Image 1 (cartoon, rainbow over the protein chains, first blue to last red):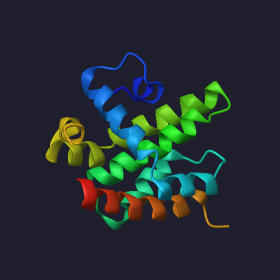
Image 2: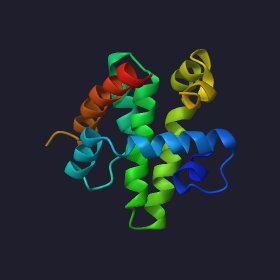
Image 3: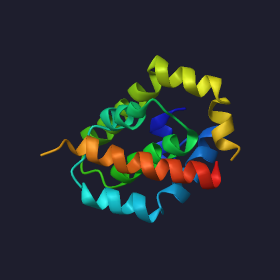
Length: 115
Length: 24
């Protein structure tokens, strides 16, 4: 996935476009919006991702929710540096072997998109 | 006091699992 394409909704391939469509739905979650509104200062997305899996579990609902909060911060971002930081931290989270190996073993991004 | 990343993550795990159960 090109996370810059995803968060900008720009020059998306079909898979990224479908994940983008799912993201959008997710960004309407009341609990997600409330969580976002409670922390307007942009946090470290890589750390958030690693904290989510700190119980030893991962699933596609968690992944979609992490992308969703990332999109919310990206939409409200106040500088290009903030957008670069979001994109790079998402890229770094999903490029960790522990996460990339889970995705590859659980249907790949195509399985996320086929939901 | 607590890192925001820890507070946010706790909530997102809970929401993510509920989304996983209902829709995934």
